[PDB]
Length: 231
Ligand SMILES: O=C(O)[C@H]1O[C@@H](O[C@H]2[C@H](O)[C@H](O)[C@H](O[C@H]3[C@H](O)[C@H](O)[C@@H](O)O[C@@H]3C(=O)O)O[C@@H]2C(=O)O)[C@@H](O)[C@@H](O)[C@@H]1O
Ligand SMILES: O=C(O)[C@H]1O[C@@H](O[C@H]2[C@H](O)[C@H](O)[C@H](O[C@H]3[C@H](O)[C@H](O)[C@H](O)O[C@@H]3C(=O)O)O[C@H]2C(=O)O)[C@@H](O)[C@@H](O)[C@@H]1O
Image 1: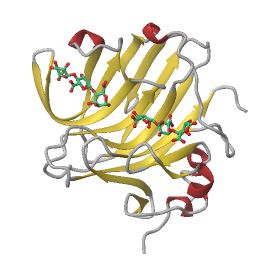
Image 2: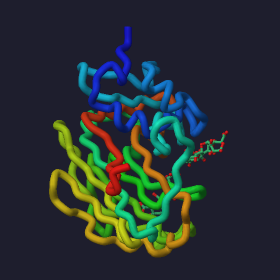
Image 3: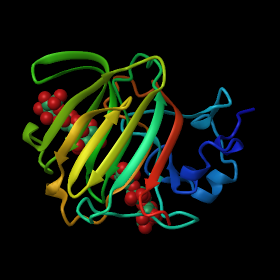
Image 4: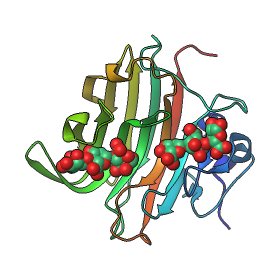
């Protein structure tokens, strides 16, 4: 039988601050249900250690969505509220099966758009350089569809071992740290000033697969939203 993620202590803080969306943005499990041992092939404890997400289908997901702690409702914060908003993770991204082309593993999202997606990418060219099997950031600086609405950055080549990430937002600027090294340093998020519906997400969100049957799979060794005010 599949072991529940809540069976160990490692993820209890974030599970107390998240709902699970699967296989779409529809609710799969409340925070209380997650802490109560919710489990399925889409969300289970692997190796007694990893919170593992799995999902197949274009634009489908198995993802945690940041909630107000202790049974609260959906959270919404703003890039310019003066507080530092921080998400941390340690992720083992396995080799992805054929047909999986891009898997979003962490986000900043709002009511209407993704401010940031950190994603594994099979193959893509950025600023004239071709990259394969790597982790990328995509930041929106507008809601348009043209390339000038995005800043896309190679963060790191995918590693077999765990890779640490940290996302920080403060005073309308974004920093991303990968394995302890700042890779994105103060990217401007001021386009989003005044949007008070932002929140963190993490898990697996499957983007533009070439087979809707192909199952994306992502293993978290650690995940947290870090509260700088210590509530
Ligand atoms: O490689 C490129 O830069 C090409 O990307 C195209 O634009 C992307 C855009 O960068 C971004 O990745 C976007 O991401 C969406 C995602 O796939 C999901 O649909 C959902 O999360 O919503 C995201 C979003 O709307 O921001 O997808 C688009 C895309 O068109 O596929 C083009 O800009 C292309 O010209 C460019 O070469
Ligand atoms: O297009 C998407 O799939 C986007 O969905 C987003 O989640 C939303 C979405 O509306 C979802 O159905 C659900 O909405 C709930 C939620 O409780 C909301 O606060 C409202 O009060 O009731 C809705 C309901 O009863 O269905 O969750 C929403 C949310 O913001 O959490 C995100 O998953 C996006 O990432 C996604 O692009």
